[PDB]
Amino acid sequence: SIIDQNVQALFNEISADAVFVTYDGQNIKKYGTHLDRAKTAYIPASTFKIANALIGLENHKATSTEIFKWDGKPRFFKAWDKDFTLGEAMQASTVPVYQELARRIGPSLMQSELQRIGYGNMQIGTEVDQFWLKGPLTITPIQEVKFVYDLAQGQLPFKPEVQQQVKEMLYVERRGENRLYAKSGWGMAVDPQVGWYVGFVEKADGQVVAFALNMQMKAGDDIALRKQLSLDVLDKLGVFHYL
Ligand SMILES: *C(=O)[C@H]([C@@H](C)O)[C@@]1(C)CC(S[C@@H]2CN[C@H](C(=O)N(C)C)C2)=C(C(=O)O)N1
Image (cartoon, rainbow, N blue to C red; front, side, top):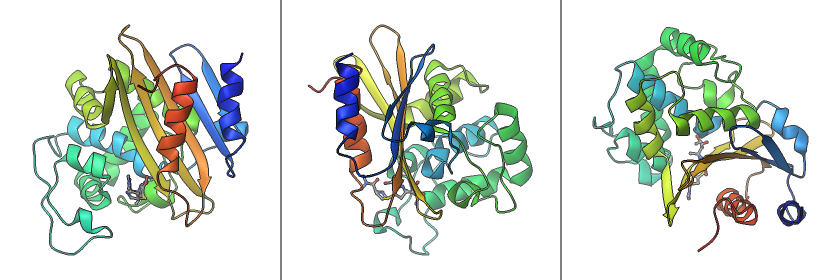
């Protein structure tokens, strides 16, 4: 149309292989500079926190009220040297809280749960707190978008109230009655490095547009670009207008 051009025009300034996928429940639409990324599998990096919190609440290894206390050994960011609920760590994207969670689940249950839901290639290897940060788990942008679409709908294979709790841990902001939910990721432990911005817009018409930005990253890049680009795209799409 003209909005496709407006969206693709945004990507004409981006000096990085990038793809942006949308899923409204019927149609996958793809935009960006390297459309083949949408079908390529990459480490989920911190976007796996979504599936990690689901599996862990579903299997009685944590609650969303439980405090994950700081054990004193300092952390990569100094904003991490605190106590966190699972929701507070989801939006701080605190990795050691969610590695502790994965150790609580264990490799056996982690593997069988990932098979049970069909997440990515469902591979975890031998390090139960490392597979999403360095492989072997990989997932395509198209898989991430359907996954978070079903989460928005409450249609993942989990107790309805577990989905609702992980859903609200992702909540970012609202504009009128439209609600943005999102989770960023930056996988530095792989070559190439992969950037994620996955989420969905819940409209007032009970309707959902899921989205997944996926792009290549290099050390030094603007950490704010993933979100600012995805929000630009959503506004050109008319899915989540600027106010
Ligand atoms: C997640 O994918 C990644 C690794 C460590 O699991 C993580 C948490 C590092 C970064 S970069 C940096 C950390 N938090 C900052 C941030 O979110 N803001 C808003 C300043 C950026 C990310 C990331 O996605 O940015 N994820």
